[PDB]
Amino acid sequence: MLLRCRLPGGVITTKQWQAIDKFAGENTIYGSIRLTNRQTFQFHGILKKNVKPVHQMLHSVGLDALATANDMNRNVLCTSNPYESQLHAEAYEWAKKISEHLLPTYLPRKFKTTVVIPPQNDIDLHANDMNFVAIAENGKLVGFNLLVGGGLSIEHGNKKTYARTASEFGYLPLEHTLAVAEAVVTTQRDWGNRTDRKNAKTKYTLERVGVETFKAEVERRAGIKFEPIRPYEFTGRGDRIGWVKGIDDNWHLTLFIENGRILDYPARPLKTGLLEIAKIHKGDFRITANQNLIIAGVPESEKAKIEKIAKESGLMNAVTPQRENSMACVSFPTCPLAMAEAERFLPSFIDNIDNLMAKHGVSDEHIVMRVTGCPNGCGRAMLAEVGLVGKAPGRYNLHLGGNRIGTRIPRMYKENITEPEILASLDELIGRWAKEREAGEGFGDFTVRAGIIRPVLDPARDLWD
Ligand code: SRM
Ligand code: SF4
Ligand SMILES: [K+]
């Protein structure tokens, strides 16, 4: 009653879309397509009668789901809508090559990989084991900076677990990408703590052996020496909602989809709308790491026809910058591990946050705000400026002090509190931010600067109070 597709970089054809739309509507309990924050999609509630039909459906359009249980990798991410549009094709080709290279070495724990195009960190590289940060010259990839060892999962009350950001190893020319990817994976395979499953992730391996030790073994196995890191900076993690110009005469329409949940709602036929777009659209779709959808490669002559369907179906309903930059995991009703609501909580929670932002005169601003239903961390709250981590029904740990670009873990601020208490705290804090912030200063950076919360500087040692 849960299927998830392999879909490197989130790129899905309109023929593939029509097939998964038909299956979702006819052969699942919930009737939805759920976009995931690893750039793929899920069905919910597949009856026993429809388990063979769904793998045959995927195969009929060239898709595979083939998970996982004995076979550990997850979907390889790729920046969906780079500002330098010409870089996407090559970066996506490399995400596909890496994905195919790592198809079945049993790993100690699942392993997550990304291809990132600065200045966008939409794929949230610090949540991932292995990250290839693209470096380009003259519109062509020349190589990657490698960052290793991110991961967000924690267990409540267990100070031996922690979220960790990823560590820079150095730069590699493009030709060494697959050798380096294999070397990182096999080093983790060999050095990971297999016995203790809560200690098996690469983030723990790196802390046990040291970054230089792991890096040296990767160099030896890959047959390379890393070069110094080549400069890169991120400016944000959000999607580019609306129309942006791509390559040639093409345009990309990114649609905000709340929680990535695609279903026909009253007066908002989101699912039928996307089907009608799939039937006329000349290009592909791209599922983003923010659970949104890009209608990619629209010729200028077709913009008006695509926008008409999107507007009439509810897919272009205006929301605040705050809502565009908020995210939650699935949680209830389908997740067996859920402690508190996330997806079903987020719309009314952000309604309340929207009122606080307006009350303090910052309705045009945003705070990267995420809700995760339990500390496994799928909603990526442990990279948010404001993160909520489910503890029990209606109760969350409130974390503060991440940043807009996702390079710092937020420390826990208040433990095991309800929504009214969270909103009361955030009302006070957003008020202070609005009045005391420096020009362009984000909410998370402010809570650190103003001494509201201490920063997390070295998570393996200082995440836990
Ligand atoms: C759908 C998604 C959340 C979303 O709203 O988008 C999701 C949903 C679930 N995740 Fe995940 N995870 C999703 C991204 C993540 C991420 C974020 C990311 O990868 O960018 C994390 C934190 C990053 C990390 O791994 O450190 C994440 C860490 C987990 C973990 C904890 C892993 C660990 O190291 O301890 C579990 C539990 C487990 O593996 O035992 C888990 C388990 C689950 C399961 C399958 C629960 C289960 O084991 O039975 C969830 C199914 C819920 C449902 O009913 O659909 N999921 N999960 C994401 C699907 C991504 C995908 O296509 O593969
Ligand atoms: S964070 Fe917990 S509740 Fe949310 S989807 Fe992941 S496992 Fe389920
Ligand atoms: K979304």
Image (cartoon, grey):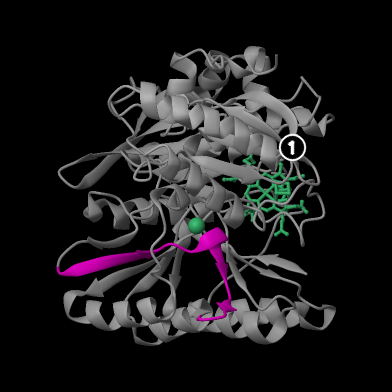
1 lies above or below 24: above
Residue 134 counted in the magenta span: no
Q: Magenta part of the protein: which range?
A: 249-267
Coordinates of residue 355 in the picture (x, y in percent): 49, 47
Near-viewer residue (192 or 444)? 444
Residue 256 counted in the magenta span: yes
104 lies above or below 255: above
| Quadrant in which the C terminus appears | top right
Q: Is residue 166 something that shows in the picture? A: no
207 lies above or below 296: above
Q: Under tag 1, what secondary structure?
A: loop
Near-viewer residue (202 or 152)? 152
Coordinates of residue 31 in the picture (x, y in percent): 66, 78
Near-viewer residue (110 or 241)? 241
Q: Residue at x 78, y 69 (%)?
A: 1
What amino acid does circle 1 point to? Pro
Q: Residue at x 37, y 56 (%)?
A: 93
Coordinates of residue 248 in the picture (x, y in percent): 15, 66
Q: Residue at x 75, y 57 (%)?
A: 332
Quickly name the residue at label 1. 108
Coordinates of residue 204 in the picture (x, y in percent): 68, 24
Near-viewer residue (335 or 40)? 335
